[PDB]
Image (cartoon, helix red, strand yellow):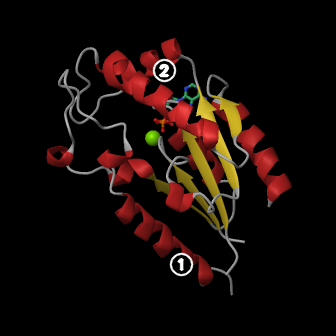
Amino acid sequence: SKTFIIGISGVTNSGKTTLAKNLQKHLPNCSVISQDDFFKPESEIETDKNGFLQYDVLEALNMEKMMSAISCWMESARHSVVIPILIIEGFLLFNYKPLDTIWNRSYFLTIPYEECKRRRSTRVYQPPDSPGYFDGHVWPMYLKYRQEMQDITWEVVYLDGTKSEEDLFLQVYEDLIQEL
Ligand SMILES: Nc1ncnc2c1ncn2[C@@H]1O[C@H](COP(=O)(O)OP(=O)(O)O)[C@@H](O)[C@H]1O
Ligand SMILES: [Mg+2]
């Protein structure tokens, strides 16, 4: 019956998947769900005035399919001990109200504008980032999300994504040992 559910959010390229993976390998009976696995097909993505595909919005995501994956994990978690841990990591978690009571802990990776743009440029997407995509869409949708975070009623731990991978792992691991 009992579970421990962790949210890891933050801007694109802030190290969410990396952190989730480092935690998983050190925590027993731990799983990870990635929001990145639940994008709608390209044809269902809206395009704005400037021709920018709206990927960085809840409407780009099949959150019904994501919820069923979380329910599948819970059912598995029930038979996993003869406390199971789930880590949900993704760029748009904490503004999704159906999940607002799920979080036992809530982490938010932050990196500044320049570093985010730098990392984002080293990654190859499907389809590739158009020129101007970061300034015309990615960063604006991020600031909109941070504005939406201002009415979150529960505690969120903001993490500095420019710290080394191990530094971030230890910081979160130390926090978790104290919460579990
Ligand atoms: N602590 C860190 N410091 C610097 N770079 C990192 C760190 N963690 C991950 N990265 C790198 O930044 C990029 C984004 O990492 P990833 O974990 O995929 O981010 P996200 O899941 O938030 O998109 C990758 O190239 C990855 O190797
Ligand atoms: Mg990721």
Residue kind at label 1, given as amino acid type: Ser
Mark 2 lies on residue:
116
The answer to whether 29 appears left or right of 64 in the picture is: right
Give the x, y percent position of residue 57. 37, 40
Q: Residue furthest bottom?
A: 82
Q: Residue furthest front?
A: 151
The answer to whether 98 appears left or right of 52 in the picture is: right
Look at the image and tell me in which quarter the N terminus lies: bottom right
Which labelled disc corresponds to residue 156? none
Nearer to us: label 1 or label 2: 2
Q: Answer yes or no: disc 1 within 8 Å of ligand 2.
A: no
Q: Nearer the viewer, residue 16 or 50?
A: 50
Look at the image and tell me in which quarter the C terminus lies: bottom right
Give the x, y percent position of residue 18. 54, 40
Contact flag, marks 1 and 2 (Cβ < 8 Å): no
The answer to whether 46 appears left or right of 152 in the picture is: left
Q: Nearer the viewer, residue 26 or 124?
A: 124
Residue 123 in which image quadrant: top left
Residue 131 in which image quadrant: top left
Mark 1 lies on residue:
76
Residue kind at label 2, given as amino acid type: Cys
Q: Residue furthest right?
A: 178
Q: Secondary structure at mark 2?
A: helix
At 20% from the left and 33% from the top, the residue drawn is 127
Classify 16 as above or below 142. Answer: below
